[PDB]
Amino acid sequence: AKQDYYEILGVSKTAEEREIRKAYKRLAMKYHPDRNQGDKEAEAKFKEIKEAYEVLTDSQKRAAYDQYGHAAFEQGG
Protein backbone atom coordinates (compact mmCIF):
# COMPACT_ATOMS: atom_id res chain seq x y z
CA ALA A 1 0.00 0.00 0.00
CA LYS A 2 2.58 2.61 1.06
CA GLN A 3 5.81 3.35 -0.85
CA ASP A 4 9.51 3.93 -0.02
CA TYR A 5 11.06 7.37 -0.44
CA TYR A 6 14.53 5.87 -0.90
CA GLU A 7 12.64 3.97 -3.59
CA ILE A 8 10.61 7.03 -4.56
CA LEU A 9 13.64 8.93 -5.86
CA GLY A 10 15.52 5.73 -6.81
CA VAL A 11 17.44 6.74 -3.68
CA SER A 12 19.31 3.89 -2.01
CA LYS A 13 17.86 3.72 1.52
CA THR A 14 20.89 5.89 2.24
CA ALA A 15 21.36 7.46 -1.22
CA GLU A 16 21.94 11.22 -1.49
CA GLU A 17 20.34 14.30 -3.11
CA ARG A 18 21.34 13.54 -6.72
CA GLU A 19 18.94 10.63 -7.28
CA ILE A 20 16.64 12.81 -5.18
CA ARG A 21 16.90 15.58 -7.78
CA LYS A 22 17.30 13.08 -10.63
CA ALA A 23 14.65 10.45 -9.75
CA TYR A 24 11.89 13.04 -9.23
CA LYS A 25 12.75 15.31 -12.12
CA ARG A 26 12.97 12.14 -14.23
CA LEU A 27 9.35 10.99 -13.76
CA ALA A 28 8.30 14.57 -13.04
CA MET A 29 9.74 15.96 -16.27
CA LYS A 30 7.77 13.16 -17.94
CA TYR A 31 4.61 13.95 -15.92
CA HIS A 32 4.82 17.74 -16.21
CA PRO A 33 2.36 19.48 -18.61
CA ASP A 34 2.06 16.21 -20.56
CA ARG A 35 -0.92 14.69 -18.75
CA ASN A 36 -1.36 16.92 -15.67
CA GLN A 37 -3.84 18.73 -17.93
CA GLY A 38 -6.00 15.59 -17.95
CA ASP A 39 -5.45 14.11 -14.47
CA LYS A 40 -4.35 15.90 -11.27
CA GLU A 41 -4.97 12.79 -9.20
CA ALA A 42 -1.32 12.09 -10.05
CA GLU A 43 -0.22 15.54 -8.85
CA ALA A 44 0.30 14.41 -5.29
CA LYS A 45 2.63 11.66 -6.50
CA PHE A 46 4.75 14.67 -7.53
CA LYS A 47 5.16 16.04 -3.99
CA GLU A 48 4.63 12.58 -2.48
CA ILE A 49 8.02 12.01 -4.02
CA LYS A 50 9.47 15.43 -3.26
CA GLU A 51 8.36 15.10 0.38
CA ALA A 52 10.72 12.10 0.44
CA TYR A 53 13.33 14.77 1.21
CA GLU A 54 11.89 15.62 4.65
CA VAL A 55 12.69 12.00 5.23
CA LEU A 56 16.02 11.49 3.41
CA THR A 57 17.32 15.13 3.34
CA ASP A 58 17.85 15.06 7.12
CA SER A 59 20.54 13.18 8.99
CA GLN A 60 17.89 12.07 11.52
CA LYS A 61 15.27 11.30 8.84
CA ARG A 62 17.50 9.52 6.31
CA ALA A 63 19.22 7.69 9.17
CA ALA A 64 15.91 6.86 10.84
CA TYR A 65 13.71 6.11 7.82
CA ASP A 66 16.55 4.03 6.32
CA GLN A 67 15.36 1.31 8.72
CA TYR A 68 11.79 2.61 9.19
CA GLY A 69 12.52 2.73 12.94
CA HIS A 70 14.57 0.39 15.14
CA ALA A 71 11.93 -2.30 14.50
CA ALA A 72 13.32 -3.23 11.06
CA PHE A 73 16.51 -4.31 12.87
CA GLU A 74 15.52 -4.44 16.55
CA GLN A 75 18.36 -5.40 18.92
CA GLY A 76 21.66 -4.78 17.10
CA GLY A 77 24.36 -5.70 19.64
Image (cartoon, rainbow, N blue to C red):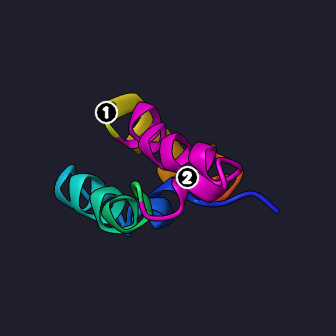
Residue plotted at (71% across, 50% down): 41
For residue 54, say whether it is visible: yes
- Rate crowding at label 1 as few (under 14), some (14 to 19) or many (20 or more) other CA atoms within 10 Å: few
Q: Which mark is residue 37?
A: 2
Could you give the CA–CA distance between mark 1 and mark 2, rounded to whole angstroms? Answer: 37 Å
Q: Is residue 25 above or below residue 47?
A: below
Nearer to the camera, 28 or 6: 28
Q: Is residue 69 magenta?
A: no
For marks 1 and 2, the one nearer the N-term is: 2
Q: Amino acid at mark 2?
A: Gln
Q: 48 or 69: nearer the eye?
A: 48
Q: Are marks 1 and 2 in contact (CB under 8 Å)?
A: no
Which residues, given as a range, are shown in magenta?
34-56
The answer to whether one can see residue 77 in this image is no
- As drawn, is 66 to the left or to the right of 45? left
Looking at the image, residue 46 lies above or below residue 4: above
Q: Nearer the viewer, mark 1 or mark 2?
A: 2
Q: Which mark is residue 59?
A: 1
Residue at the (48%, 66%) spot, across then down? 7
The quadrant holding residue 10 is bottom left
- Residue 11 place in picture, x, y as percent: 35, 63
Q: Secondary structure at mark 2?
A: helix
Secondary structure type for disc 1: helix
Q: Which residue reaches farthest right? A: 1
Quadrant housing the N terminus: bottom right
Nearest the eye: 12 or 32: 32
Q: Position of residue 22 (x, y in %)?
A: 23, 62
User: Amino acid under label 1?
Assistant: Ser
